[PDB]
Amino acid sequence: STEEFGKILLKVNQDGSRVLLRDVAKIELGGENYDIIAEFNGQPASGL
Amino acid sequence: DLGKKLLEAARAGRDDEVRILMANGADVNAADVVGWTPLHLAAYWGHLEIVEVLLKNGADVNAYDTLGSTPLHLAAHFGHLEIVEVLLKNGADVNAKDDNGITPLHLAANRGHLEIVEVLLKYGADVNAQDKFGKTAFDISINNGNEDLAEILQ
Image (cartoon, rainbow over all chains, first blue to last red; front, side, top):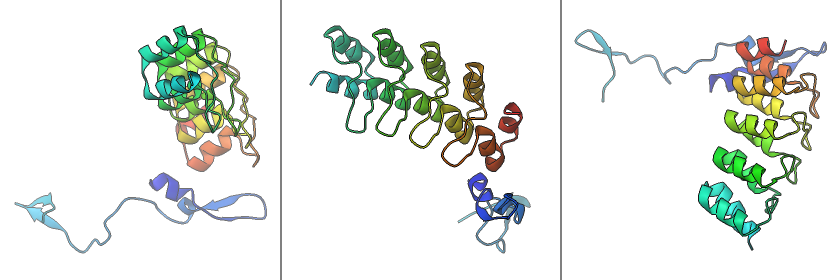
């Protein structure tokens, strides 16, 4: 889950506070590659 | 080998066979290799109808395995709301700490079972309760980034 990746502990500061991955990055499910996008009769679509 | 058949029946969810083995007088606190009673297995796999039958024939509700985990730990961890109530109503230790200092609230908070967390708190579940790492059920909610859970524990 994105929630599990978000709370990955990058480091703990000297004052006790801790830097999670969600503090330095946005966590979402997204394509391996965003180059390829298809439309069927001008309507958002995928295909094989 | 009668209390051993009860363990297998309790896990399988065979409501009838448990009552049949109970009539013949099988050990209700018959523990397996890892120290799980029939009540443990029923709580984990979520056989509420069996949990009621076991507790009615005096199944040790505060029975703990070889790592100090009780049926309430399992019930609260795997989101078995009905079983958590039935356990607590039959005098289950809500502040029960395992070998790691983890309580049913810690497990309920971790998996984000918001309903069960409220039921534990209702029966006097210690919110300030820490584990071996000095982490409360609220420290879990902030790290998990749970909005709904964090508001309940403050």
